[PDB]
Amino acid sequence: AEIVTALPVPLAVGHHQPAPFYLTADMFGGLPVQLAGGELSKLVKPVAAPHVHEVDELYFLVSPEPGQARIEVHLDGVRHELVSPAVMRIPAGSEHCFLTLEATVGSYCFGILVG
Amino acid sequence: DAEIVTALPVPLAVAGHHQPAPFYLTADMFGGLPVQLAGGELSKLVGKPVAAPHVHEVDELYFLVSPEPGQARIEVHLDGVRHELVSPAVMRIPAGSEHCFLTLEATVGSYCFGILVG
Ligand SMILES: C[C@H](c1c[nH]c2ccccc12)[C@H](N)C(=O)O
Ligand SMILES: O=[P-]([O-])[O-]
Ligand SMILES: [Fe+3]
Ligand SMILES: [Fe+3]
Image 1: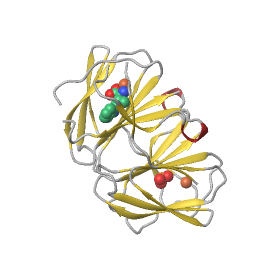
Image 2: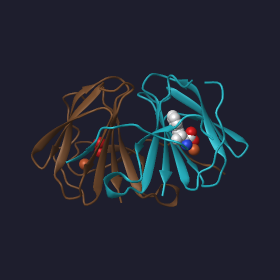
Image 3: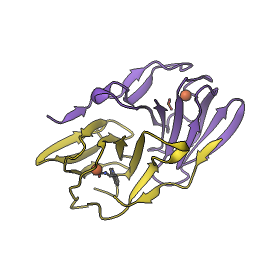
Image 4: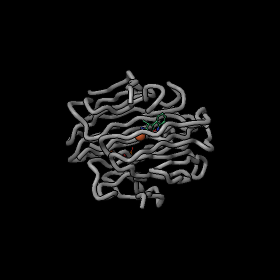
């Protein structure tokens, strides 16, 4: 049985700290996605830095009950306010970041890099 | 301009599942995705399996996560063998393998996501 428990894996990605990855491209002989992120309640953090990926990134915002988490996604000079649950596509090459406005314990934003 | 999906989750029928499963990523989104992602918060599912044992023809990953490590625990049945996963954990279910999970323990904010890998 293939079980990975040494998680998250910190990987450096404009981002101050290594991002915490729960799926990496090399797991299980190869995955078509990578998945990073974490709980938002301790992330509610005055600044966020813009950055670009060479692949598409999907933001996946979720909370135990709908509406309990809220983020601002900055995408190429446009501010977008999203309420959980939400999924937003960041096209490869686009400068982007997000800020957590509100989040209950158990709210997550995952960044999913699509190969 | 920006592609945003908020009509979520998308209920989709999955083999063996009593009710439609809540999907947050589907294969047709954004012109095509190599994965589908379904699942949700486990705090009300302790003791209550969402599905009978079932088989997919694609690989499925269980992604178990909680705000603090250890706050969520599920039992995965994999071709008649029980495996206990403690958050955070990722488990690969090879295509063709009979499987299901039972929630053993979950705080508010514990999730199990099933990721179908094309
Ligand atoms: C991986 C980055 C991320 C998304 N959600 C997160 C939650 C906590 C810590 C990092 C993240 C992503 N590339 C971004 O654009 O921020
Ligand atoms: O019900 P989901 O974990 O596939
Ligand atoms: Fe990013
Ligand atoms: Fe399954």
